[PDB]
Image: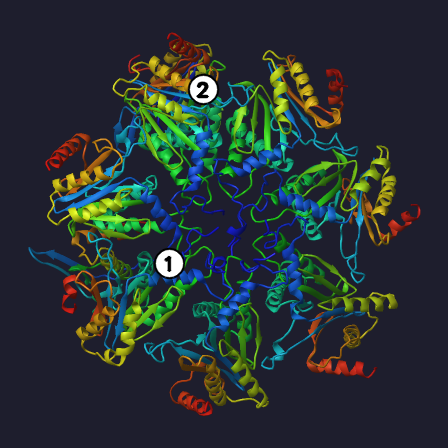
Amino acid sequence: QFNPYGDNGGTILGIAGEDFAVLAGDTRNITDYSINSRYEPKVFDCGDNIVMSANGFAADGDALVKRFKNSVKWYHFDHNDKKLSINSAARNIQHLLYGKRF
Amino acid sequence: MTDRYSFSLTTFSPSGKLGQIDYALTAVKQGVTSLGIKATNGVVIATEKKSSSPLAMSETLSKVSLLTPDIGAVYSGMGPDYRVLVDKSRKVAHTSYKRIYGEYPPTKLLVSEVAKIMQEATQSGGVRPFGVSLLIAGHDEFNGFSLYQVDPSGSYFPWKATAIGKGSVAAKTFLEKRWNDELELEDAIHIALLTLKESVEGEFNGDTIELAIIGDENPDLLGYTGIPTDKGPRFRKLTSQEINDRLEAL
Amino acid sequence: FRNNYDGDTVTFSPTGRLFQVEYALEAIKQGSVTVGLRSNTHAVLVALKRNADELSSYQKKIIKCDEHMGLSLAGLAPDARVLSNYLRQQCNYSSLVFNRKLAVERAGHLLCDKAQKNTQSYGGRPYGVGLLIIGYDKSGAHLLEFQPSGNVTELYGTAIGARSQGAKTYLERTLDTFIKIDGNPDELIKAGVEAISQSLRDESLTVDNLSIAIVGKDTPFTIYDGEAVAKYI
Amino acid sequence: DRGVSTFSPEGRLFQVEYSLEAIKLGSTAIGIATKEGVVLGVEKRATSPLLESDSIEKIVEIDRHIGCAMSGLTADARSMIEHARTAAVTHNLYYDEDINVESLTQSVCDLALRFGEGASGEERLMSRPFGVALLIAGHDADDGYQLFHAEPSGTFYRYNAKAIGSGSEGAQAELLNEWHSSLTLKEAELLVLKILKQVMEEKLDENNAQLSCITKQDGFKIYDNEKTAELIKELKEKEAAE
Amino acid sequence: AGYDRHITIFSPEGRLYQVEYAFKATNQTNINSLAVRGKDCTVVISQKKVPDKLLDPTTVSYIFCISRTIGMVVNGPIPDARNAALRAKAEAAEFRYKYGYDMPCDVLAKRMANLSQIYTQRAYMRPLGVILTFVSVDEELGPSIYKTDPAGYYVGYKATATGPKQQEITTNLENHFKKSKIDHINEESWEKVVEFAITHMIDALGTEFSKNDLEVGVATKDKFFTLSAENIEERLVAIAEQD
Amino acid sequence: GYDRALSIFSPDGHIFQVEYALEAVKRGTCAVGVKGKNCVVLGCERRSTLKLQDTRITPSKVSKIDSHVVLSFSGLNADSRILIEKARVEAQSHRLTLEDPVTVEYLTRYVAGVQQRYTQSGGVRPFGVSTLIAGFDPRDDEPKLYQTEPSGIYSSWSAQTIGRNSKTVREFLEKNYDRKEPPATVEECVKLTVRSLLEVVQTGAKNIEITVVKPDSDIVALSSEEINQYVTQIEQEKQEQ
Amino acid sequence: GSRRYDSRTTIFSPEGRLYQVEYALESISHAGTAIGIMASDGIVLAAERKVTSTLLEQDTSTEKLYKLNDKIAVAVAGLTADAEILINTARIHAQNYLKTYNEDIPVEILVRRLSDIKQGYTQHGGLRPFGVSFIYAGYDDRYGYQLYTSNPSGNYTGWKAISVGANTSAAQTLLQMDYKDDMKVDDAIELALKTLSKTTDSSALTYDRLEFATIRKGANDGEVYQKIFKPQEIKDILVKTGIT
Amino acid sequence: MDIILGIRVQDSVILASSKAVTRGISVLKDSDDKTRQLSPHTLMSFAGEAGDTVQFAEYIQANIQLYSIREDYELSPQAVSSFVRQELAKSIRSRRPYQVNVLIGGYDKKKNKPELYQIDYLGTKVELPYGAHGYSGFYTFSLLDHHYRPDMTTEEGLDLLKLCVQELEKRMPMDFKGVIVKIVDKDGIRQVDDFQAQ
Amino acid sequence: GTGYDLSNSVFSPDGRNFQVEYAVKAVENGTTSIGIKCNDGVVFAVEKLITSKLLVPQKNVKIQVVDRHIGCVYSGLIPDGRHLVNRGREEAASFKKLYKTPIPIPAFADRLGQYVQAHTLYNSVRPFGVSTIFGGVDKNGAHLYMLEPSGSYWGYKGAATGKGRQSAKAELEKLVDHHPEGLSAREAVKQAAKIIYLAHEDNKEKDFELEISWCSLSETNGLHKFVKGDLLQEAIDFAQKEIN
């Protein structure tokens, strides 16, 4: 039967300093025992000083990042280029995700 | 696009009349005469085939139609409106009765169905009433023979005999005189031909007169044999020849 | 005459006119003046913001549709919102699906067709706003003028709104000069402010009255207001 | 007849214009903004002595930092309020933050032109425009204290002071002179109360008038009769003072 | 109240003006047409007037091929003519698909007639400014001519004519049949029936035709086709060598 | 299907269909409500254009939305049914979803909304009805009296009247009811109501019907006698002078 | 657009009246007269057949008295065609009530639903109202004998005696003159016939121009019975009441 | 399942219903009232699926109360039970059916007799002197088949019940935490708050 | 009576459709545009009025392509014209999708025809304020067509519409007579540039820019393409010369 999901490996890590923060990840993309790419960025700068990474099934990972960035775009259009606070971003992502709870 | 006429085109006037139903009836008045007579063992309905050009073949057209094997119709008014009503009538007799009880509807009820169609054309959005009146005749086991008249308003009533269209007034009077509750079918056919003769200007023969009867079962008109209970249609349209032969004993 | 043929947009006058559309165009002339002009490197918008009382604010005339495109308005502000918002989606659709920046020429075609739909079906109403769209795409800088009729035109410069003819003439005259202001925005902006002050009358352009927008080669469509427009008044 | 979304030869929408007329016939409503908060005032206007004057709600809360005053056909304002409240609470659910006063305003204005019998732009179902105007006041971390005027046209302006309703034209003239960037909340309270007294057919008292305000500290509060009655007294006194 | 003349509802006299005005539009092309029945073929004649010199004459026509066996000639404006034709072609294809045999000329007529009757009763639908003449050689009925109008009326004919000078053409044929005593043109080949048709057209209208002044259609057993300029030119000569 | 905008603005900023709706109210029979200190009373007049009616069955003017709230009206009868039914359903729904019967203020605001909605929704005409809604909130003893009209506006009253000659009877009440000291008794509260109706009913013992609502779903409609008696005692008040 | 031909059948007049309803009533006023008289032991329905002929088949006819249930019937005044559309939906509503509750539908419940349907066409839809007025004569065990009347507006009320159609003012007065509470069915039957006999626009009141029905509870049974009189039946009762 | 019992005596109907509410391994409540009053003289006990159970009862409640208000009259038990059987018969063939079984007990003020109705989630309705849903019937039907008489008094009936509840505590696997009893008669619905030792 | 020109689908007493006729007014008032059917393709030309020096030269292009082998040019309400092309584009795509073969010019014609004819059937729509000249090369030759706001269309050797509609029709008829053996694509281009210059005298008040496109079997491979650069200048001169 058709299985809509897949696994592209990868691993990400995020640590928060006192006045800074870091988000890292390997740049390997795999499928079973094959390596699809030795360099395929996984951590992105979404703007307003917010870095993000959705790791797991790459297709879903990109769809999500893309959707979020698009959210930040409209946030600017809507609230006169107001900077999207990291906590607001967090709440917004929760809705993006839970929106597909099923 | 999209029918934006979702409102009634037939409304009430300050006087309390319904214009379109009135005008519609006016159109019925203008139409060719047609009549019906109920005997003790049959019913007959007739009209005049007013050919609209000697180049036109009046045979390729029926003013007297079969609704079910025991119900026929005829009109006065606008031909195209009658035509679609006959199709709708034949269908509804099936969809709303034969397909449920496995038997054709009884006159009154089928007539009741037709009436409903017209009534809706009187209140539904974006439409005009039907410009015709029908004389429906038929027979059913529990009601015998009957003759009903259905007006554009959607009303209907039973008749021993009646006429509609052009010379209806004259015709009605003539019928009230000749009719009685002891007429045999043939007598009524004769009377019918007589009454019709007055309303007919030009030619009057089996090729200008259209007449049908709801009489006995025509087993010979069934098409198959081997089923006792199926006895054949009671409705039978007469042939050009059949008419003339009677026109001589007129 | 005209009274029997202006009840809606689905009716033509005996001379082949669409009044409802024409009345819409009127809303624009009644609107505050705004000017647009471009060179081979930048495209500029200059608008005169109008206000209600002296206790009120000066309603915005310029809207950004994307990093490389934007427009100024004259007429029913609500309609400009609807339209610029539609243009934003189209800019967005091009990025997401084709990873391509929507060309100004195409944005124009899109606008035209959207407007047109509201002039041939019963129930609709033409839009009552005029737009001047500037933008920098693969084929350089661009300037478009959008009318509610549906006609979108590409020009070197233009102006719309009350007393616009003043500025339009000035541009029509200065043409060969500003069309060559390349690699120097501040100059194209001045030629912009000058052209617009050619339509003044009532007052003089102040700091919280003037509004400037600039897009170009290495310039993401940005807006300037108040103190920001100081160095041009 | 003539479509509800028709354009007049002068370039205006008939229904919207006529809508503004009904507004002129509405109760008076005034708003004054100060670096200490915003004050909203309305004329109850009771059509009888038997009518319990405090069941007259012409100043409502949108959120803890947003309130508004209405003028004109007020039954119309109901769905605008519901929308405004939902918009405010919703924005919070999705962004975990307060909705900016301007955006809340802009949101309400978006319902304005959503009317017709088949307008080719979406699915604008609402037979006529709204016959009520609104004065929206609140505070937010981006632009502090704000006062907004939202109309059935679908447009809105920001004012330092604004009056709408039957006495507006004159009252606005008053404000034009009276207002100044250094007013205090109290000053604005008396000023609002004073202008209402001038334009009102009735004698201003704590029963046919009502005040309220929005401060960053306590948010939107509506003054109860007692608090108002006093301000009224304090006003009569300073007036007779000269 | 006076709008009983703008949409299809009744007037006090019980008339539908819009239907009548539609009839008026049928003569707009100023073209006459006529059809006659052979012994086993049906022919339809129609005037063809291509005035402009910039027109491509080959593209002008009021004769349509609805199906392998049914042809239709239209008296009325071309945009309504083509709308009607398309609808008829579809009704034709669908009928075959659903019932497993080719739709009979009379039936297609009755179907188009009922379709018109509807525009007569529904207010948002305007009638079509055209009269439709269907012809074929029905596998059951033989040579057939059925015509329908904007009123939703239709009937079969021994022969028929339509257009501005319809009445002249009619009385002409009327007389021919009053004479012959039979309901068709007792001729075996269609060419002779085409010639008869063209002839009486000339006699009634009192006019001479060239090969570009006519348009001919023929229906035979299992096929309806239209003649080319030349096919006519040859037919025209034939009648010429008789006068 | 049909969506013609029937309630629209005119040059002077008026919605005529809504105004005409009010005219229909002015023509309907009269209705009145006065709140006491522990109860609320509703009184309505009965037309006399025809008399040979069967009052047993004939629908009465005061309806129960729930067991603690009632509603009377003035205007088109048919239109009242639609409103009553809608409010009745909302009453049960509110119990179900909030586990607590609607308050009088709420049930009123709901009915007003329905009316307001019918004034800016294409394809429908406004309701030719104005209403009086009274009762006591759940677990509360303070009487509630509210009024609504076609425009969708509503508010509370100490006493109020709607319908024909309501102008009269209102004047009567305005100068016969003291908020300071409301009819402290069910009895004197029913009296002030009959008195006020008699100002316009013009001798109609069978033409007047009363209904008293007390806290905790205590609603009852007086019979001709109980009413007739009140009428008798009142006529003596006049004569004894 | 189409707004041009829209009669707007659902708006108020400046006087707060509904044109269409008004006009529809005007229509009903020319309809055959129908009276409903409710006695202590039953109810009576009588109506005058508008337009008749020697040829009209009367045994098969029914243009005013319709059976809705076994314990409910109606007399009609207005457009027969319109009446039927409504009569049928009522007969259905009656049955649904039974199917759901397993009890016969209370007379008022059936009346209210029918009246709500009418009210609808009065408030939305751009359609014309039904040109019909009903006199409902039924019986149930929650109110016993009941007599109701409903018209185009969608309003309905109860009556002891009532008439609809033409010459109602005259008929009402005559009824209002001789109706007595302690009346008996046959008393009502007579009052009924006599009232018509005086309002009739015709020469005399013959059976062939009448329809009669009674809802009585035949003592020798204990159940209420509906009886729609046959031509020969009306003819008899006609002679007896002294109208020959 | 839960304990849902019903017995109709001479002039009243008695309904007994287990008070326990267990969820897996833990008994979350011992004072649960598995009943809803539909009208002053009609009570309905129910047992079944976790959500369906209450949602159905309340839904049925709301509708009967609405009919009462609208008609200013109280529907007979028989009628109320017919409305309920209908609702379930619809549910049975719907997308997601209600899995609820109910006992309906009421006093017909017009016939002046008590009535008991048993209806299952399929829409099966039957009128009985005594009935039960779930397994309860399995040990109580023979008791009642033995000791039941139509003219018993409410007191006699309440004893017959105690007899049943006893057999149930003796032979049934689950600890249902006792029952809540209610009587329905000419005067309405009242609860026997003293059966935990009656 | 009168007013038979206020609703779009109404027949006047003489059988006309005034709204459609008025639509034509919008057309005749527009810029002139033409089509010339040569021996293996077709050429399209159009007048582009320079309303001011502000219009960027060579920009606001009028001629449109449908698919890859069809060319369109129209006079009148431009927005209406694009709307028509947009419909042709989907109309063509739909055809190719199911039949694989790019849509035959003749078939495409009727697709546009039925669409336009449809906007003269309802009073809820307005007729197209444009006359369109379009055509191309297909399986059997080249075809030229012109569609009228009424929905009417026919095949042409030459066609014109707009302001200079008569100058052109005159010139085109001359070409027909002086080339009974056909005109080449190369020649049709120059001959087209001239006709525009001449037809521009009925608008000589404003300056103009020329626009030509062609679809030739031997010149463009049966594909539609705009005549740019040199070949264009050449035709521009050929006209400028014979204009004097």
Read off the residue under disc 2: F201
Q: Is residue B13 above or below residue I94?
A: above
> How far from the left and from the top, in percent, is residue B27?
70, 48
Residue type, mark 2 in image: Val
Q: Residue at x 35, y 44 (%)?
A: D22
Read off the residue under disc 1: D11
> How far from the left and from the top, in percent, is residue G19?
53, 38
User: Crowdedness of circle 1 by 10 Å Cα count: few (<14), some, many (20+)?
Assistant: many
Chain letter of mark 2 equals F
> How far from the left and from the top, in percent, is residue G115?
53, 31
Same chain for the residues at labels 1 and 2, yes or no?
no
Q: Quadrant of residue C81?
A: bottom left
Residue type, mark 1 in image: Gly
User: Crowdedness of circle 2 by 10 Å Cα count: few (<14), some, many (20+)?
Assistant: many
Q: Quick one: D40 or F107, which is closer to the camera?
A: D40
Query: Left or right: D178 with respect to G90?
Result: left
Regarding mark 2 in the picture, which secondary structure is present there?
Answer: helix
